[PDB]
Amino acid sequence: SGFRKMAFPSGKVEGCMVQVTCGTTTLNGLWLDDVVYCPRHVICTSEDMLNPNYEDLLIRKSNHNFLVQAGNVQLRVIGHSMQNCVLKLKVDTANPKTPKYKFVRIQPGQTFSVLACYNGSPSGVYQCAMRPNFTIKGSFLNGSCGSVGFNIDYDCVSFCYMHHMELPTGVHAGTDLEGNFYGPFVDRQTAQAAGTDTTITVNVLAWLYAAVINGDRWFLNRFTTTLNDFNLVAMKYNYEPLTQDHVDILGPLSAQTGIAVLDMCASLKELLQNGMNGRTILGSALLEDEFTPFDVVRQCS
Amino acid sequence: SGFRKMAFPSGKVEGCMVQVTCGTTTLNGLWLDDVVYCPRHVICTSEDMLNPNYEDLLIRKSNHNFLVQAGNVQLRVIGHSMQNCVLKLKVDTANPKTPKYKFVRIQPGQTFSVLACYNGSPSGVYQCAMRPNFTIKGSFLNGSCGSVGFNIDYDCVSFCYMHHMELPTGVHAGTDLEGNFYGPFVDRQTAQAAGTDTTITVNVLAWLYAAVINGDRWFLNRFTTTLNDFNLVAMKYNYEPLTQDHVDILGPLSAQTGIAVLDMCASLKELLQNGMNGRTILGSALLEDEFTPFDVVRQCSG
Ligand SMILES: CN(C(=O)Cn1nnc2ccccc21)[C@@H](C(N)=O)c1cccc(F)c1
Ligand SMILES: CN(C(=O)Cn1nnc2ccccc21)[C@@H](C(N)=O)c1cccc(F)c1
Ligand code: NA
């Protein structure tokens, strides 16, 4: 019993974190096989950051302009290339701690673990979701760029995020490991702003299912809803639309608890209307949207 | 910016987790140097769990009755003994991944990371506090026993918890690594219940300081208070008493933010008295008590 925001064990990722230095800038890189991945903005100076021409900045660099430090050891850079918004530094040693891995681009609503790192050394691990507005609500200080997000379903690490920047509202933006940004963001210091965020409806429902599995039914009611009426109400509280895909995805949790998906939708409508009236659900006084259907099955009996 | 419930990186502890099997029971052990530590209840069957005589159950076991698996390798047990409520299995190989470590006993209110494991295979990590009633609000299924809690204080892992049981309210009880229970619990199937819990006041204040650092200031006010008046308020709301030591510990955060501790106590008094009036603090509608002052400084400063 219990329900916690639970991260993956971080050791497989810790063994891959290095420090990348270019000029006066130091940040984190990810060392897999004989390649070090890091944000391309490492090559920017103070001037550059508003309108950097990365191709022009990079052509001016040699291999030995990049200092890569893995623990106490310097790695030798023997090649470099840029792919989208990541720098790939080819090094002369394959990382002996390279885990089985892959690169996956995730969708909004997906969760992952972040290993926050400074100077190539891990500081902490926490669980995040990709928000509907393509930001993450992380915890990051200066020097954290190049920290990564991952899942480890099985023994295979799926890298899905690399940290590039903090927006003015204090939320975070980054790329997949192919260097493509999530959302409309760019790696420039121009004024850009996250869109209005919404609540991840399918995850809230998943979490209501978790509460039922863990023995709590107080918030259920005798009613049902059509999918369309559910969406008409939920969007008035800035909830994401629920799609038939989402309904299908919740089918296993529906079967385990004996509560139909649109019946749970009816419960959610009433919760939005009434609030909790001094009660909690799995120890929360708010409706939690950073647990996916898959996370609930992973964690719950 | 941002403030998350954050665990220590778990890699140093992952390299020490093994599977211990005795009869039909499989659970997790901690392999350090040439000893594997696990809950002594591993030697019990269901009937034994009712009224175990551990000494008597153990004398009947041979070394080879304990199957210890580190990944895909079986370790050979060459000795076994008990210390309080933990079994110590001496094995023929020192763990080459043994980190620098100590065994430390923590106090209620202190936080730590838990590496939850099943069949000696780490599955997740989360951050816990030791509650004033000596339980933890963990997340554990059958097979989780022997999962461990820890802090890292440099390159040194301080092991502070090993999981033994779930209580009827769905909270968790366990020992330090010397096998001494936290709380008035025993390792047997009998009627056991957590005492009524309280809120960890010094931690709530720490978290209010985190909120201010991150730009959430709506709850600050022009008032201050005294320790004695505030403590009358804490007691009324089932908060732990705040001591001078607590005030001293929060001194750095007071200096950084310009909010004295008793000034922040005046904020907290008003929150307890009036509620939050629809608003949140760091995304929470309740007052969070599982960050220590040290946790806030560690996360907010480096
Ligand atoms: C370098 N930048 C950070 O936000 C870096 N960072 N990340 N998390 C951060 C958290 C706190 C402070 C800084 C943080 C920005 C910036 N505005 O300067 C930037 C400029 C140019 C190209 C970039 F891709 C990013
Ligand atoms: C083995 N026990 C668990 O609670 C084990 N466990 N831990 N977290 C648990 C979470 C879910 C289910 C079981 C869980 C009990 C029991 N009832 O048999 C017990 C027996 C003997 C000595 C003990 F200290 C406790
Ligand atoms: Na005040």
Image (cartoon, coloured by chain):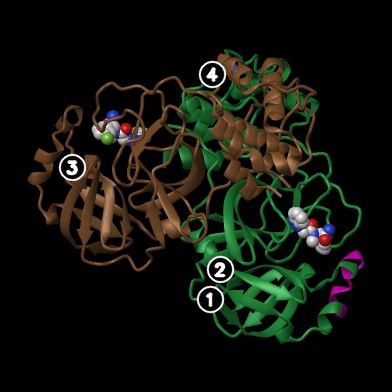
Chain colours: A brown, B green
What residue range appears in magenta? B48-56
Residue at label 4? Answer: A238
Kindly tell me whether mark 1's CB lies below 8 Å from ligand 2: no
**Rendered location of residue B46, percent (x, y):** 86, 67
Q: Chain of mark 3?
A: A
Mark 4 to mark 1 CA distance (whole Å): 53 Å
Disc 4 and disc 2 in contact, CB within 8 angstroms: no
- Mark 3 vs mark 1, foreground winner is 3
Instruction: List x then y, in percent, for residue B93.
Output: 55, 83
Residue B64 is left or right of residue A21, and the answer is right
In this rendered view, identify the residue nearer to me: B57 or A86: A86
Measure the C-alpha gap from mark 4 to mark 2: 46 Å
Q: Contact (CB < 8 A) between labels 2 and 1?
A: yes
Q: Which residue is mark 2?
A: B16
- The image quadrant where one finds ligand 2 is bottom right
Chain letter of disc 2 in the image: B
Nearest the viewer among B179 and A153 is A153
Residue B23, magenta (yes or no):
no
- Same-chain status of marks 4 and 2: no
B271 relative to A119 in the view: left or right:
right
Q: Distance from label 2 to label 1 (Cα)?
A: 7 Å
**Circle 4 sits in a helix, a strand or a loop, which is it?**
loop
Magenta run includes residue B54: yes
Residue B277, percent from left and from top? 65, 14
Question: Measured along the vertical axis of the image, is residue A27 above or below residue B230?
Answer: below
Per the image, label 1 sits on a secondary structure element best described as: loop
Q: Nearer the viewer, mark 4 or mark 2?
A: 4
Residue A139 place in picture, x, y as percent: 45, 37
- Element carrying mark 2: loop
| Relative horizontal placement of residue A78, taking residue B157 as reference (left or right) | left
**Label 4 with label 1: CB-CB less than 8 Å:** no
Q: Check disc 3 and report the residue beneath it.
A: A43
